[PDB]
Length: 85
Length: 52
Image (cartoon, rainbow over all chains, first blue to last red; front, side):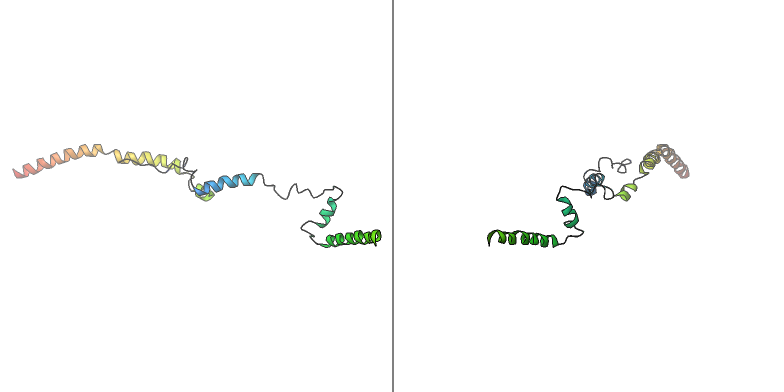
């Protein structure tokens, strides 16, 4: 009966659809992400932290300090042998 | 989603012309309607003088 008008009804359409929820998720997801590996805190020491940073990161990740811990029990219990028997 | 929104870049600037020129080309023909009145009148006049 007249010139009907759905070319411009986008302004209040852009809430209900599914990429709108993904869009408002990931524009929030992107800003607080640190850019290029920044603030990783690669240097730390608390009298036991260099042990962790040298041994217990994902780079080395070897169980040989447990060996040393086992050696520590060889340092401990055998000396407890010297304290008991 | 960037591509889907960028499909709607220059729609409004062109559809504000579409709306207006479309309804004008609909509704600027009542002149032709009132011309049709005169056309059918002269049609009847030619028909009856053909009868005479």
